[PDB]
Image (cartoon, rainbow over all chains, first blue to last red; front, side):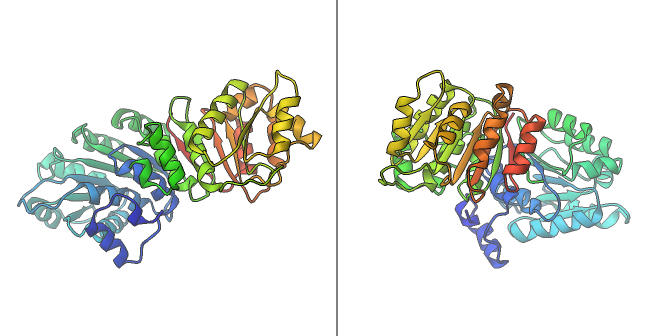
Length: 206
Length: 206
């Protein structure tokens, strides 16, 4: 099945066409029916498999545009590194032209990302330490999140971000859809899925 | 997504409508994109989840009708019991009106099933002991199988059918699509997947 065979809005299909993307990879093909219907999913997949579109497209489809100044994000994606935050933000921005995506990460000053968040965001793509910082400062507000994504949960554990990831998920409403991607599933990640996801389907392309 | 949203031929959609089936269950929704494209899949699912349509529909779609007298089956489904063989045969027959389905099982005489197989079959749904019996008698010919399904691999192991299942798979061409459904994955079933499937995607709705 091609992308145009799934329930994706015109702006998304136009964007995909514009980059020559037509045919979902296996993780995408298996995930989309469920993810587009708002269901929770665990994606066991390594980089290179297309996992980023597997969650970017559901975010893109679910979120209508908003001009609301100062608006709080309706999607949160956590990543273990700045490199991946930037990569995911760029890809989401590409398939969701209708949305304002803000990347948040450490190893820099606080000022520029603060001002972007205060201006308004539809989706935030963040490393957990700096996200939690802005959350406790009251700059990042997660009370409106509709989709939460943990991208490389196992790497976030290896980096010592477990308490940050849990605090961030806890700040989102349980009415949310949650998507978790991880090549491996250490016990912490299994517990995290049990506590913070709703009957998730597991799809493994390893 | 509804059934009519997947690439299924008119006779299949008419049949599904005729029984009031419209909306795939999660295992079906995740499996169909891949299964309909001819890819191998492991479905970790218990009875009641809709696993039977998850493999019956791909068989139905892939196999065009044939009138060829004496023809050999192009699909094989193995089940651990007579009860499940009959249940699966009835469901396949319901969604594939264009196909002749023959059920094969022990705890009865050899004569009636022999004559059905010799007359011709498009799909055979079988318990492994009796299937292997007919195979070695030369009554069941598996050289034309395009889709092989192991339905409840773990139960087939518990019943002591491992060598029968392996012999039956070995008699099918490796060009086949293979689908394996099992609530649990004991080491034998993992080895079986490694030997007899091609880069299978695993979908777990447990």
